Length: 148
Length: 143
Image (cartoon, each protein chain N blue to C red):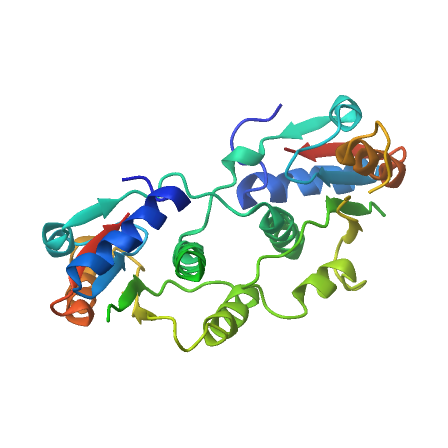
């Protein structure tokens, strides 16, 4: 039972090197939502913990938008105002089309705010302040609800 | 305060009653600015949001591809093919079921089990197919 995140590049890249040199073939098993069968877990040479694989921040606004779509699915308008951290292409293309498929009578809109540069010794506090200025501008006089 | 379906469902009807339009604000990874937090009439926590299970095998495949990229052993990713969310790119399900052979590892998708009466659980049947695929390989599990 390996602690932490053994799939993370500093650990996995070194472990793959060892697996290649060992020469034996490797199977990495992932079950469904109910998990792996006891026989699979008993056969394992290494056991990694699924719970440590957390939700990437760019998907937060995706899950929230879906939550609101579902809630509207079962005059006031709602805006999701979110910082647009870059998500993977295999999500972004699908998410743009997902939003386009919403019914026209759904009073929901996603507004994405440009994410500030987070590079070499960037001042996070001022980056956050500038994102917040743009978020509050988009919200105008609406009721403000924060999710964090 | 926790973001979830029952609390969101109740709050949405409440929001209509005072009539004002509503903006839900999500910051960057480091959080919201002080001015955003000060302006909030209501605050929700996203702590209990988790990665959708079908994306687990996708993120693991990404990790494997990237680790191979910076380094006669064959590695197989043997994963139950849980249905993709509605917002993943069209054709991605098919891509994961027909993973390209020029990738540095193989992706074997176990069909997500589902009428017939028996005493085998769905995960018992999946587990039989997984151990068949794995054979005499070294086994790593993620669960």
